[PDB]
Image 1 (cartoon, rainbow, N blue to C red):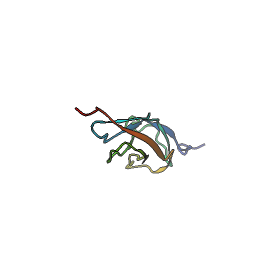
Image 2: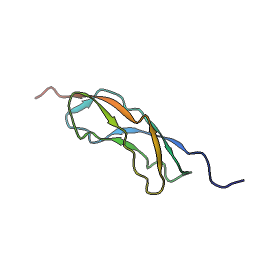
Image 3: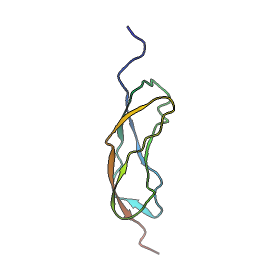
Image 4: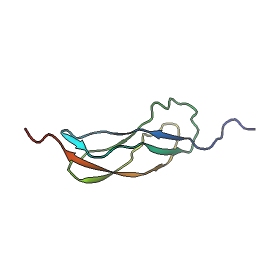
Length: 96
């Protein structure tokens, strides 16, 4: 006997790598992520929802990158799961 007010939505975002260094090739697959929001968006063009990690650095090492979500100018975020991931970086093109 109520209009809105329903459990938080659980949508999965395609984890894509951004700021990918040049001549660099990652050695690990990128899996989606499960996020929770303390709100209710039956629509809001869910198409425009993605998660991206920062790669402001490059070096053949196993660096742990934090999951950075896209701020929503209307609703609030609750948390992420996982919250951090390990991606192996490897060089490419054996010189000239």
